[PDB]
Length: 209
Ligand SMILES: Cn1cc(-c2ccc(-c3nc4c(CO)cccc4c(=O)[nH]3)cc2)cn1
Ligand SMILES: [Zn+2]
Image (cartoon, rainbow, N blue to C red):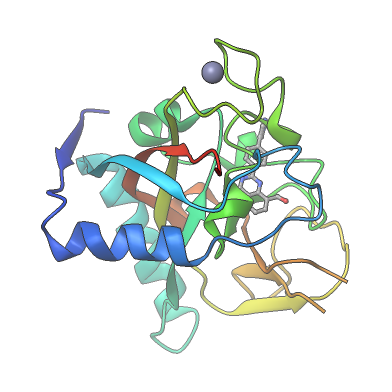
């Protein structure tokens, strides 16, 4: 339950890399920016490493189970995640019982390779009502947050179109929605312990001008 957030220095290459994955994976979205807001760059305020003994225990236990079940290859990937429930994720860990039901691959926990895709879910599905303060889906004042996660993919099952499932197919540990049709790739897990909220990114979207 006890989380420790260690601040990474802007001069540390651990921090520089995380910002590089965030900034370099920004892509033009089909909604014209309705959910995330109009922007071309981020203003990264703080990058923190999330430390929780039990969450790391749950994840490492599962990683071992997935590894054994997939020829000793857990197939981990660092993907982004945006959710209005960041606080509960860093303290209580991801919970499949809070799976995005409305998803194209059903009730799973969704991650993106593109940071801009996760930014549309920072304030809820389709950006919700936006920032709690100024009710703006495009707010440039409020500090937003998202996670850059360690995700245990195991044997991924590739899909190209909407296929609703509750759990990953037999013999598989995850679903990947590939851009064929799809705008950007989306990664889906059906178990909370197959993701660890490694990095906590406090940032702002930048008003172009
Ligand atoms: C119960 N509840 C679940 C939610 C919530 C929270 C987060 C997401 C979510 N979805 C993503 C999708 C889905 O297309 C693709 C790619 C990335 C993401 C992502 O970072 N977060 C979805 C839903 C709200 N309330
Ligand atoms: Zn605001």
